Amino acid sequence: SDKIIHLTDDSFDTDVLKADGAILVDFWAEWCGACKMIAAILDEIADEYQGKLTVAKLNIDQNAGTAAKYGIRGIPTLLLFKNGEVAATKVGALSKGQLKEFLDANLA
Ligand SMILES: [Cu+2]
Image (cartoon, rainbow, N blue to C red; front, side, top):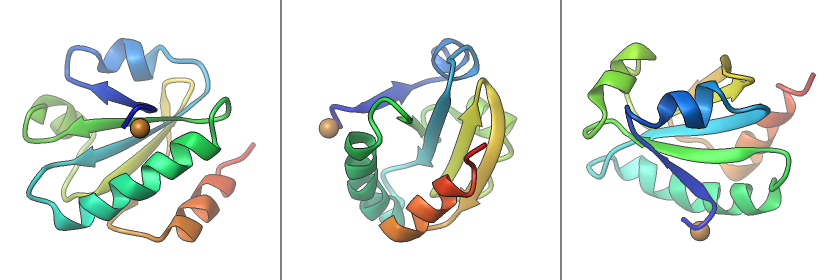
């Protein structure tokens, strides 16, 4: 958790939309079982990709406005932003290897 940005409706603009570079945002909630493994994988990704990718979390129960703005329909959902714009999304659980594939697919 030490390398994960904690986002809210009130910090999303500054921390994501105005952030230079790539940010991977995990839309989650406590009641989401699949979200638990995603979190464990994301800690490793955040560590391994330091300097190249920032990882962040947005709790959809607590920040329904942001969830609505991005059309979140189910969780987990990962949104990859580059320079403040959505570059890719992945809905539903995936393995660490699949996530690394998903990220590689988005390299310019
Ligand atoms: Cu940590």
